[PDB]
Amino acid sequence: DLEDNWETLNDNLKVIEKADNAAQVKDALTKMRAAALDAQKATPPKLEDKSPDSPEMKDFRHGFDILVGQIDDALKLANEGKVKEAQAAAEQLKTTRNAYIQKYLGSPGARSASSLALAIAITALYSAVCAVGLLGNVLVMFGIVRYTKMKTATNIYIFNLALADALATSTLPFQSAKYLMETWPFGELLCKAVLSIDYYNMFTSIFTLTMMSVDRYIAVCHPVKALDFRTPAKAKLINICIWVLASGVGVPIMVMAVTRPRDGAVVCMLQFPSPSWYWDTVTKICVFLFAFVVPILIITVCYGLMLLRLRSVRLLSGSKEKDRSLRRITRMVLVVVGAFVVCWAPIHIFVIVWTLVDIDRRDPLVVAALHLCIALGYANSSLNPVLYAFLDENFKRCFRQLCRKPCG
Ligand SMILES: Oc1ccc2c3c1O[C@H]1c4[nH]c5ccccc5c4C[C@@]4(O)[C@@H](C2)N(CC2CC2)CC[C@]314
Ligand SMILES: CCCCCCCC/C=C\CCCCCCCC(=O)OC[C@H](O)CO
Ligand SMILES: CCCCCCCC/C=C\CCCCCCCC(=O)O
Ligand SMILES: CCCCCCCC/C=C\CCCCCCCC(=O)O
Ligand SMILES: CCCCCCCC/C=C\CCCCCCCC(=O)O
Ligand code: NA
Image 1 (cartoon, rainbow, N blue to C red):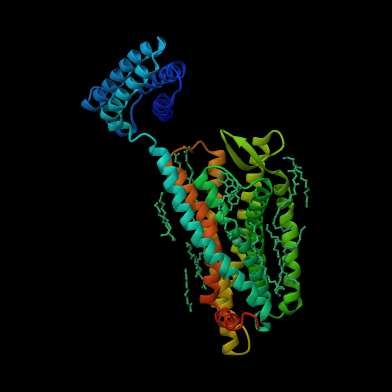
Image 2: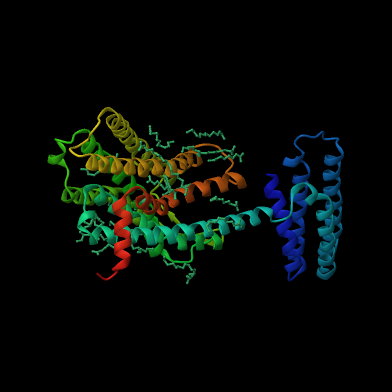
């Protein structure tokens, strides 16, 4: 209510300076006056702790009284067709606004300024995530393809995470541009690509982590039975099944993703069939369930039992060297899974809150928090290759060898 009044007041001052004619000035003055009278009835957030009779609230009201009277005088000029004189009076309005109202409401366009500062912060973070995650995950993929010692079932699942992570990080410079420009300049096909990739990363990542966790559970807790379940070839086939299952959501996203005009700009968005708010809500609930709660419950059972096994048995296999290896690989999986949960839980919860709950969605701290949770979800992509290199001696060694011989 007050926020909107303050913007309209300030926006219309600008219209007046830009006006071609008296009618445009009269119209803008008329809106400024309406906005001013509404603002005058309200309490600034800063003054919530004060009496209506305090020197602060007296001052705030006095300012709008002065402003309204100046608008009344300028309207008489505009009504009589005197555009230059009307425009000149709008200059005096800035003085009043600055001396009395900005005191309490903050600088005009402070909200816009925060939006821009956030977009610049997002761009910087997204550029870092993109560089580390794209380059890092491409190396992981080439490394696994190149080396025989790298083709283990666990690492075939890691290949799947890397593919998703490479795709997602490749979108980030486009998303940055969108945030800075406050519009989508890239056309509909790229919109479909970016939205689809975004959802495929979300679904394939968690499906892959669930299968990695089950695979590791089998390896650690059922080592004899494991021979009948675990091979690199089987993990590769499960990866394909993961992408096919994820396409259940992916292909509908591909179809529904469109560019639409919205408030002078172009938005890249999902067009749900009617009633759109309903299918949006159903989809968000299903994402919360099947991309977050359900796989995390599965993983938690496997995770807890792996922890119990690791402390309840002296040796997981024949030799201390190999035991050590199985324990190290298991720890790496547990860290990767843990890092995923820490990076993605905040945004999963926040999407549900934003969609279903009556929060203040235009509040800058709430918007910044939301965007930081989104960024944290992407940052998981850049984190992973770093985790693999520090937690698995074979990744470290094969990263070095790949770089020694890029072409063999
Ligand atoms: O239902 C989802 C649950 C979690 C996420 C999303 C979901 O629908 C997308 C979506 N709609 C929103 C509506 C209001 C506020 C935020 C979002 C997001 C965030 C996000 O863009 C994000 C997360 N990306 C992934 C990105 C964090 C790395 C995947 C797609 C999407
Ligand atoms: C498939 C599993 C791996 C995928 C990895 C993600 C990469 C997505 C890349 C490009 C999407 C381009 C989409 C091409 C456009 C076809 C959809 C379409 O035409 O939309 C219908 C229209 O909007 C109303 O009916
Ligand atoms: C905005 C969309 C841009 C998407 C494309 C850029 C991201 C590229 C991602 C993955 C391609 C890398 C595949 C490397 C696997 C090794 C292939 C092989 O050697 O057989
Ligand atoms: C870019 C910001 C990313 C911040 C994410 C922080 C990542 C660390 C998160 C969780 C680590 C979980 C540790 C799991 C313990 C291993 C169990 C064990 O081996 O006994
Ligand atoms: C690693 C586990 C962390 C999980 C905690 C999740 C916290 C982020 C999720 C939701 C926060 C929602 C906050 C909404 C504040 C409402 C303010 C308002 O408008 O009144
Ligand atoms: Na991912």
